[PDB]
Length: 127
Image (cartoon, rainbow, N blue to C red):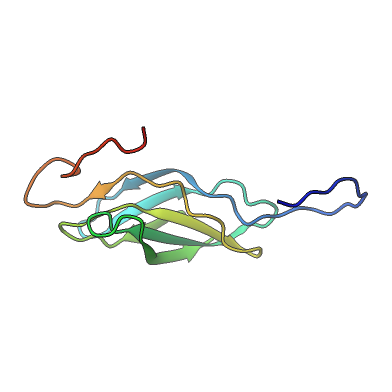
């Protein structure tokens, strides 16, 4: 990482819009779930857009793809889910600076299948 010190100058400092938190999943339509995220600090540079991504845990866990984005004003976007599909949802913030890192990682939303129980394959993840 960089390393400096001293330097009198009334200059600001940015670093893309920090990642969101408290990520949650709530809906009430039918075939369209809404992803509620909370954009933390903007770091001088205000949010302009919010990209999202997900990873097919039911297929290839760790493969994030392009889901959808929105304006830097809203904080709720609809996600298209399918039956027998597991994956996470990561929100991203993009401003004049650039695109920040993806949100931590919301809960594992598993659609309805031919069997109850959230995740079919449980395991000691993160211990």
